[PDB]
Image: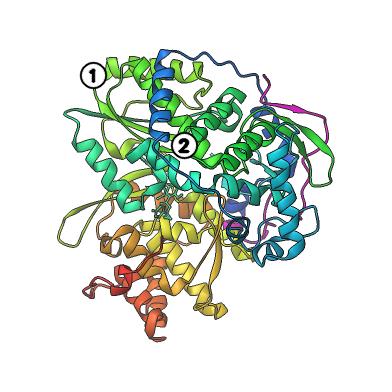
Amino acid sequence: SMSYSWTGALITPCSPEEEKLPINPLSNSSLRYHNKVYCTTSKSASQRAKKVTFDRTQVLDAHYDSVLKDIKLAASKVSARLLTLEEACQLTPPHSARSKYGFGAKEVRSLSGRAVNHIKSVWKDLLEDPQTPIPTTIMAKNEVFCVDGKKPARLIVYPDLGVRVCEKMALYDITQKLPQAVMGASYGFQYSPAQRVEYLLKAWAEKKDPMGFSYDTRCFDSTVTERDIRTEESIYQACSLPEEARTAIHSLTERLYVGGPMFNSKGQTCGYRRCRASGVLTTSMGNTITCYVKALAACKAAGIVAPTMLVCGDDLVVISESQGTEEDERNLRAFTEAMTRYSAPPGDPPRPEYDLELITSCSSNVSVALGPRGRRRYYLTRDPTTPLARAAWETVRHSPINSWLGNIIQYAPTIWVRMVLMTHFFSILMVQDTLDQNLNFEMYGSVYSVNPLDLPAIIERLHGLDAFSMHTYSHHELTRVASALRKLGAPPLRVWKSRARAVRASLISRGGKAAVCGRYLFNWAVKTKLKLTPLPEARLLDL
Ligand SMILES: CCNc1cc2oc(-c3ccc(F)cc3)c(C(=O)NC)c2cc1-c1ccc(OC)c(C(=O)NC2(c3ncc(F)cn3)CC2)c1
């Protein structure tokens, strides 16, 4: 069947949109930035709709059946509970999109009578009706990118706030338990960046002759079939559950997850979906389990020797025993053919790598830096151009949600985070006098809140003390930040190093947590190094 059907009505915005920042004609830097940086808007929504609309074909085999049976068996050992109406209301984030029924996240969170009783009828309706399609809204995401053409806008498909609370009642406990239970160590979302690196280093070292590859499915959400979604439901039903959860899970699968009509921001019918909805509670878990099932089966079909797998939604990495370059190349082609048969076709074909550092997954790669005594430290990095471009977007566009503080947290050991992002961020917090204030930031389709003064403790907990002493960066990391700065029209590293010395001194002068930030985060900026010791604060819980 077709992944989507369309009526011709536009995917409409709800906010003012901007494809490009206005150019300053007397600035060459403004010109370089204008030539390279763009924001996705509703205007490209139709181009995305064309790319994601296609017929799916699925051919399953004994390799697929065998893997599916094993994950159902592991799922059968899990016991999960219903969340009460109150717990599910409490799990709603402060600014979750308001309901069409005249109530927002504030009424849900505070348990206001009308919001609670509206959700109660949505819940009872799921128990008595297993068939009526649930309506959804389709919206074009506004994301900043750097060219090399332009990526069209990604689409978000989500049900009403009242339905979102009900999904949590039925499946929240499952999302917190099922992935780790059925995938074990392969479950990608259980690791901090230092633990992920440790996992990859152990996977690499345990092979006699390692080979690794990453796989990208072309438009994964659209490749998910109705049969794939009903299979996810049978995985969920393999768990031990209250009968009320079983009924609600079945109704959610048939009325929402398998498909349904999509409406734009104006209430006009946009189309009909017959694939994965991007904005449902089960998107991340469903994608991770389904990608894992299809990939493990494809590994068996291709004759991949001793695979160690790491799965993050549709992002997958397989580290295995190399059979030599010719056989590895034949095996990756057979893996791709099996993946395509299972309806998970490739975007870019996979390539075997014989150095862990050469694999790109979740836009990232492992890099090596030397410590002050010459010890090799391994950490995750990425090309810094798009994160730096996103950081710059907000200097002319003061957004209430920062789209680059997530980079400081995830990529804290990197040259580009330490020298540029940290320097710029702490500078702007001191100019605005917002240092000690909690701020909102986006991280993998979620709006988190963090206090900037807690950054040294958060970083040590997620990366270790090593994040504050990556002394000698690789030639590639050095070239990557220098080219990114040049391409965006930004000042070079020598300027950032001078600015960091002033930022370090200004933070130290404020004392307390601001002085800890200055001493730990900017030790790279001084020749007379302080001896950085473990933070007792890092021995606290962020998760
Ligand atoms: C570093 C850039 N990000 C990432 C870099 C990555 O590089 C590879 C990777 C690269 C090369 C390889 F050869 C193999 C693999 C990844 C992979 O697994 N591909 C299969 C991968 C995933 C993320 C990622 C995604 C979502 C997250 O979050 C959902 C997080 C996170 O770390 N979130 C945080 C947290 N999560 C869990 C936890 F317990 C503590 N902290 C801190 C807030 C990270």
Q: Can residue 185 be seen in this view?
A: yes
Residue 518 against residue 106 in the figure, above or below: below
Residue matched to label 1: 323
Magenta stretch? 1-30
Disc 1 crowd rating (10 Å Cα; few below 14, some 14-19, many 20+) is some
Residue 482 against residue 297 in the figure, above or below: below
Residue 518 against residue 127 in the figure, above or below: below
Indicate the colouring scheme: rainbow
Label 2, label 1: how many angstroms apart (C-alpha)?
A: 38 Å
- For label 1, the SS is loop
User: Callout 2, which amino acid?
Assistant: Cys
Q: Position of residue 473 (x, y in %)?
A: 28, 54
Q: Can residue 350 be seen in this view?
A: no
Disc 2 crowd rating (10 Å Cα; few below 14, some 14-19, many 20+) is many
Instruction: Return the disc, 2 or 1, that comes first in the chain's sequence.
Output: 2
Question: Quadrant of residue 48 in the image?
Answer: top right
Residue pictured at 47% horizontal, 55% vertical: 485
Q: Which of 197 and 313 is in front in this view?
A: 313
Q: Nearer the viewer, residue 22 or 270?
A: 270
Q: Which of 388 and 233 is in front in this view?
A: 233
Q: Where is residue 86 in the image (x, y as percent from the top left)?
A: 61, 60
Q: Confirm or reject: label 1 Cβ below 8 Å from ligand 1.
A: no
Residue 21 magenta-drawn?
Answer: yes
Residue matched to label 2: 239
- For label 2, the SS is loop
